[PDB]
Amino acid sequence: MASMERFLSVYDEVQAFLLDQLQSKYEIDPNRARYLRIMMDTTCLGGKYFRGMTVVNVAEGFLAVTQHDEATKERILHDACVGGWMIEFLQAHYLVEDDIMDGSVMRRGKPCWYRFPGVTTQCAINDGIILKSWTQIMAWHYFADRPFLKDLLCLFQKVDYATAVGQMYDVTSMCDSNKLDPEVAQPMTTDFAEFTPAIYKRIVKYKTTFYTYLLPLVMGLFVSEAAASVEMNLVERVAHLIGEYFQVQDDVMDCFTPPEQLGKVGTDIEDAKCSWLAVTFLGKANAAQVAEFKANYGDKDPAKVAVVKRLYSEANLQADFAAYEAEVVREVESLIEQLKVKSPTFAESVAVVWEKTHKRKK
Amino acid sequence: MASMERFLSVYDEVQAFLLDQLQSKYEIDPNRARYLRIMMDTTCLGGKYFRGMTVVNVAEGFLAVTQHDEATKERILHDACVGGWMIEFLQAHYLVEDDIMDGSVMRRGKPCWYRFPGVTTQCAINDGIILKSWTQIMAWHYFADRPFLKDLLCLFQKVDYATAVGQMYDVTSMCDSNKLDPEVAQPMTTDFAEFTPAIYKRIVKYKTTFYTYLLPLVMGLFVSEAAASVEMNLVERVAHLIGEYFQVQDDVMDCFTPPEQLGKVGTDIEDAKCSWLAVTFLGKANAAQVAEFKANYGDKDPAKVAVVKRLYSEANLQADFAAYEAEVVREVESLIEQLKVKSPTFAESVAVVWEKTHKRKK
Ligand SMILES: O=P(O)(O)C(O)(C[n+]1cccc(F)c1)P(=O)(O)O
Ligand SMILES: O=P(O)(O)C(O)(C[n+]1cccc(F)c1)P(=O)(O)O
Ligand SMILES: [Mg+2]
Ligand SMILES: [Mg+2]
Ligand SMILES: [Mg+2]
Ligand SMILES: [Mg+2]
Ligand SMILES: [Mg+2]
Ligand SMILES: [Mg+2]
């Protein structure tokens, strides 16, 4: 796609500025500059760029239906790219830490950043922190004169906070709430009482929906200066729904999608994560099925993992997924329909975003 | 001290707001709210609060020499406390990650946060991230109406970035620059060619001086609205000097100060850190001394650590420290003298900050 290459060109423009600043104002040596360049490329590139490209196509939508000088058209497009990358970089930040947390071995077909021989966990933690720091630097540089600044930084902060809170919920999802004690080591849940749709929804919302759909959609609105034209309660509502779906997809892909296609090696079962599959299974399984699940979940043992994957297949889970997908298509159509009232151009943007998500394989 | 208890009361006011927001807008359950409260208390409290109390006494300085209503006097003091805590929280953030990175066992007399049985490294990484996130939340809440907002956030971002960059330099200080390769595992330096005053100064500057002296001093100036009265080039110059000293202190304390007094268990030697002691030793040691240092540095082996501590003691390092301290007192007096020209009230503030630092034991 031609549009994806134009977005990727602003990355090179962003990377060159970021590395020159390091050299000119932070006294970095060539080899450490090289290291961070490699770190940037590995962590930030290789993905679908769904999040970056959403802020671009929300922005383009308005550009087709708005009178602007050629120069303004150009600057809004450029703004959409920097906004895109900020998000991309913000995700990169979260991925790096997520991988050390979930103990993953592979991201986007290459090894996980911390698993690079010359990196190790002790560098990666800081590398991630720099990735987040970058988002703010490229904000204060590029958007220094822009009206939408205070508002962009405020949303960024808040979206970021939700993500950290969501991450906290997720990494402690295999614990019993009432047992949580910083002084006593945490045992897995034996009863799985916190594997409810409710508690799962709560997790997904904060860890996924804010940075994945809310942020790019509203960021496209900011760069366009079109926040006022749409009803923000709908955007929050649509973003949390497509966001929920996007994470449900990610969960099934973890178990049933081959790594070569996925680019990721599954880790949920071995980590006893409160995934949609675990929750949905427990949502329909019988007494014998449940007991066998309890005796097998949360182990790195290839046999116990296989017993669970068989338990999922037998429970006919891809039937439950198609019934969930059917109900989401309804509610997304609904909300897109609602969005036409005030902003037809943003309503289609959401129709396109939903389409690309509802279609993904990796 | 009475002033330290008043600052600590705003912490309780900050913590209560932060935890109520979680409950009201982020759907947190009592036990997870309890967890973060404990996490906040352990990471943020227990320290000297040098950084928080500096923004307070810079602010008070101006208040004694400026006409203000009782209400304004009160609001500026309150602002100084929130500014103080932001910094305290920003440090807390860095400490948590620093401890996993340096592999430390003890912070402020208690175990390192990640070493709490009920925490583990996988939670701690995110906990740290939340600590940083908090600083921004309490910024956007408390300083939403304040003129100094854009300027405070901009400095915070930049100071934060330097710290991450400084951290990057520090964790890779036992490597050879030219060998750094994300694909090849990193061997210790055998030649120690990057153990120069220059390279050490470069490290300390970015990892310590920005968040420890620059940030609180200028933050006190912002809350007072007094940035214009002082010359910023002097503040940057004085903060990087006292900051250098503060880190030099931290290095000697690592080796020669007993943990019971320090609250920390030393880790530099075992990690082959580019510390002031290592650099200063190599700066005066002979051929036989150097070779023995090379064959012993960077090991967790109690015997090899002891051989190094003896090498430091023999090289009469506390003579070199007193000559460095003497030269810093000169240059700090100098800069304080320079600061009297435009701002006598801030000049004393720096005279007091230097005094407390030059006096510390822990
Ligand atoms: O399966 P992955 O690693 O793609 C994941 O969705 C990433 N991720 C998603 C949301 C927040 C985050 F920090 C990280 P998860 O959390 O491991 O499921
Ligand atoms: O000895 P410590 O742990 O007090 C240290 O100064 C902390 N610290 C200082 C600066 C930045 C940072 F992230 C952390 P160091 O780095 O381990 O020497
Ligand atoms: Mg995760
Ligand atoms: Mg993961
Ligand atoms: Mg997953
Ligand atoms: Mg360190
Ligand atoms: Mg340390
Ligand atoms: Mg130290």
Image (cartoon, coloured by chain):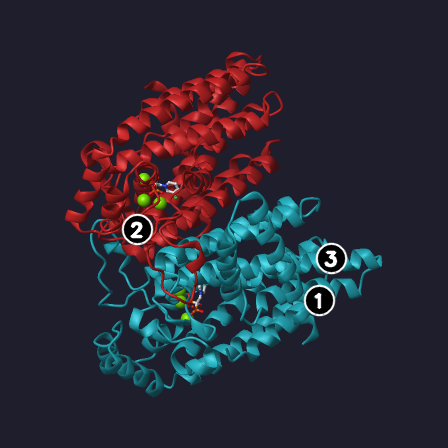
Chain colours: A red, B cyan
- Secondary structure beneath dot 3 equals helix
* Closer mark to the observer between disc 3 and disc 2: 3
Q: Any mark on residue A31, and which?
A: 2
The residue indicated by pointer 1 is B340
Residue in front for this viewpoint, A282 or B128? A282
Front residue of this view, candidates A12 and B268:
B268
Whether residue B246 appears in this view of the structure is yes
Image quarter (top left, top right, bottom left or bottom right) of the N terminus of chain B: bottom right
Measuring from the top left, give residue A362's x and y in whole percent: 28, 30
* Same chain check for tags 1 and 2: no
Vertical arrangement, residue B83 with respect to residue B284, above or below: above
Q: Give the secondary structure at mark 2.
A: helix
Q: Residue at x 42, y 33 (%)?
A: A244
Q: Which residue does the numbered mark 3 point to in the structure image?
A: B76
Query: Which quarter of the picture shows residue B100?
Result: bottom left
Tell which of B220 and A267 is nearer to you.
Answer: A267
How busy is the neighbourhood of tag 1: few (under 14 within 10 Å), some, or many (20 plus)? some
